[PDB]
Length: 74
Length: 418
Length: 84
Image (tube, rainbow over all chains, first blue to last red; front, side):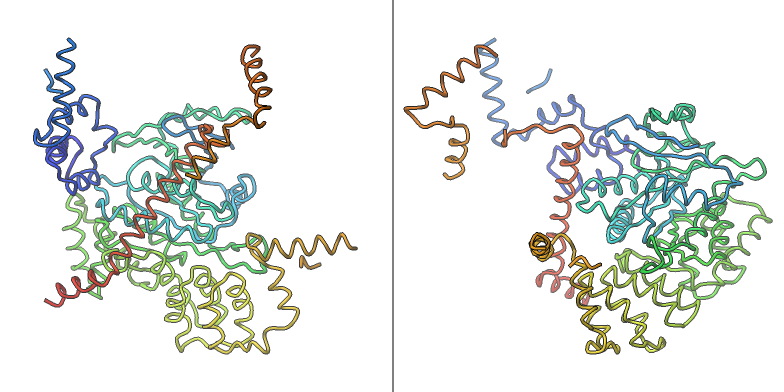
């Protein structure tokens, strides 16, 4: 038996590590994205980027610009 | 006790309902369904007889079931009799039905999800107790856990809320059985000219032993039954017993104990054993649907209906209702394999009406089949019949508009439409 | 390019210059005193259109998957695995 609360951590792990098949499997097995994806969780997803892809460098540039103009990495 | 419900939530929807007691005549309920709520007599009735158990369908089996049911129902006007409570497989079926209703280009063909639910299991019943004829009652939708009280599904269009019988706590089951039997004795059309007997069918999804009496009563009413292979409950028991081919008291008792360990009552176990034996004794009314093998719910529905008809009798008139169903669903292969296979003698006069139906509704495969089975076009196609074919155009194609323009010109220059 | 031209002449006032002066004066006077594209829909119609688009998307994806299952390569792979 699989509950939504059980798969939350595993859903996060599959979502961060780019495993679309497992995301599809978990969604079909009771994970309710409406329930699961809060704004805090979306920001957590944005923070845990691979640090080797374009989005990481772009967000780093944006953060440097914000700091120069002036908890979570992004 | 007629009223309307205005569901409040993510998606605003309006739903009708009527209170009814276990002592009512089902004829009144059918009359209000057809006339008061304007529901056309269905071309197919499918009743869900499970899914309220704690254990639920496997997600792949669940989505295949809803997809197949909706796809089979969309062909004609179908009713999906469910316990209209937001829980389990019922919620998914209601969601699929409403989604299909919204994206349906043809309002003529409609898939209606009727809900028959007990009064004692309704949440916030006093909220809908108002039911002002001018002002529909406001109802909030809440996805409650298993528990013992649920909330009415927002996606179910119409409801039949039955009161609990003071004698026995099976008022809803008896009402469902009587409704199905009464519907089985109606005609698909407004008039009995091109109308068939409404094909009523029950689908079993992970039954619990408390439904065996009602299932047997339905079988005694001579209505087909569909069993999901992977459902989990009594469905697996039945499919395994069919696989074995024979049922013995020890074998079925062992299966009952293994599948449902919680139930430990010698009298109840013996009664369930007898009920299973009596249910399987019919056999012709039982059909197994295995999505892992067939995955075409319409095919299994048609096979079950024709099997029931063939077990009933062999006369050509009896098969004629199943023949019109096959014509409606473009199941030339199923019709050829089941109806037009040796046993049934077929005359030219028999197929004339069905030939007309297949010809008008653009079913070339059935036209070919009927021509090869004795229909003589030279005999069949008279000038009057050709004019009848020209009159019954789809009203949505170019020929209809062109003929309408020609008729308007003829009338301006100045029985049958064209 | 034709889309761009049609949009531009859709937004344009209805009188060709040098007459345009009249339309501009009318527009300014009305603005001081007081579409076929980019229309907003009622909530019910918007919801129905969203649902219809989702249903069409599901049908399109199902058609893709079906034509993939009955592709020659997929049939061969299935046959090879099953015969083994």
